[PDB]
Length: 212
Length: 205
Length: 222
Ligand SMILES: *[C@@H]1O[C@H](CO)[C@@H](O)[C@H](O)[C@H]1NC(C)=O
Ligand SMILES: *[C@@H]1O[C@H](CO)[C@@H](O)[C@H](O)[C@H]1NC(C)=O
Image (cartoon, rainbow over all chains, first blue to last red; front, side, top):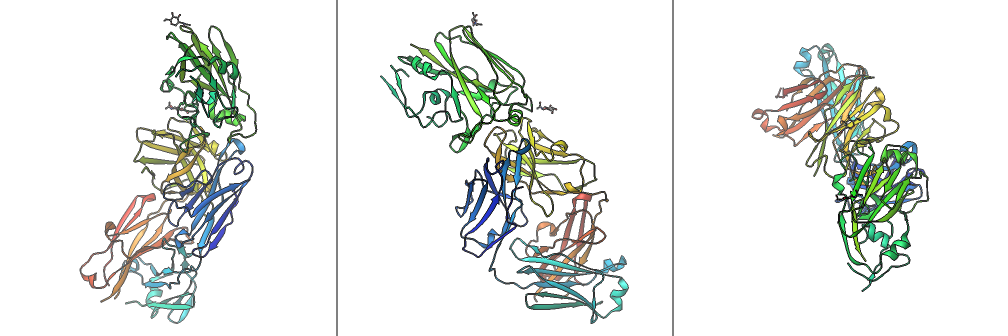
């Protein structure tokens, strides 16, 4: 209902501004609030009454409004400010309600590279005893958030029965993903080994497991 | 002995929160900085100013406790137009009554002046900006305020209409006063938009 | 510090009624001039205010939801609650309770603070399904990774802890994958000293509240 840029970015120390465009019925007539949502948490209040900060919100966050538009300025940008920022206002239309902007994902660029730890697990005895077989490729603590996963049986590649999550932002601004390869117990026992190959940045790592 | 101020007589008698006992006359700024925090009008203002001359003995007393409203909300009647210490407030000697549990029952209150001094009693009416505002505050769409003493008769109706914004508010409050004589009673009846007395003033001339 | 806690996550069948409760602690729901609010986040969209309610009963709702929404207050339990009727998949969301702290007018309150941790409500006709849990055994004077695989549950979320919460260093619980079957699976892994493998016990604790399933699994070498 309120319009925000879907993304914004800055490098540490910079000032970044996040805009919120409304109408006469909402921003034009009523106080604006801003909310910050860090990854994994509920939104928290950042700005109320257009430009007031609650206790524990530093001066670097500055709210302003003019006409039917509002703006949030974040000075001295820090890596911990990566979050979704939401504007909100009362809207007078149709007897009234709170409305929110769509949110702006703020990324802080220039963070230090970290290559992923790749762990590959074979199917457990218990799962094999239940007549199923899953290989589990765990990929954690990498930055930035793009990875490629490929699987192999012996030396030949395998595409069928693979499920891979989208890279997800941890609390420490690094990323996690996983990939699952479903096999019959028989395919697991028929081959010499299976492999998970993860490429991130310009590095490729291959892990291998074999029936014991 | 005179009384000088940087507020209006209206804002001082109503208890405007932005504003913090015997005198010959009152002289007030033409344009005080603290008049009516919630915008509106004060009826028969000059007549009241002239009456408050050469007054002896002036004491505020509680005549209708804010806590005596059992079926209306007395705690919601605040506004960002009337800030006190960065939080929304309201004139302190009258009560902006609100519906309670989505209901606004008809009010029928009387106060008999059982003192021996004259009492200056103040009350008001709220003119909302639109019909949706009227539902949100009072529930009842069509409302009245009836006031009666032995010398006075009011049968008021709020005007629901959009005005230009003043202190953020496009609605209006209008205030009235009377001198209640000892052993006379003032009678109020309302189903909405009533700004009720809480504190009144003893007057000796 | 007032604190808010929504009731547990769950499944609701289409056209039924979603019911949630928020428990307030550290202060009285009837103390102060606050409004008690519900706000939801539909997956991959934004934030939508549902409404809020005063302790003595009056409430204000979002007009797009008004006809299906009712809220109530229970001052003796220090709780307030939300009923959303005739639900569809459009009502799948994380539901947050929150306190609107700053009155600007008799019915307009701003500054949602604090918020609860949300609660995920999934609207679906499919049946709830508890997970199967399998150990991911470490295979090794350094460090070893061990974990547990949480297979085939519905709906989200599950939570995983290790040794009842006593073990937090090195714990990574990964986001779930959504299988083409419509079931979720996830993994949790912890990194520990290789030396302690013979002497220390590692148990992962899997909780799936939508089905009332609690499963512990010992993860041991080989
Ligand atoms: C408020 O009104 C509802 C009807 O919507 C009624 O059921 C309830 O008893 C009332 N609450 C109180 C505290 O009187
Ligand atoms: C006020 O109270 C006195 C004493 O009880 C009574 O005599 C008088 O008639 C009352 N006045 C009115 C207007 O009811």
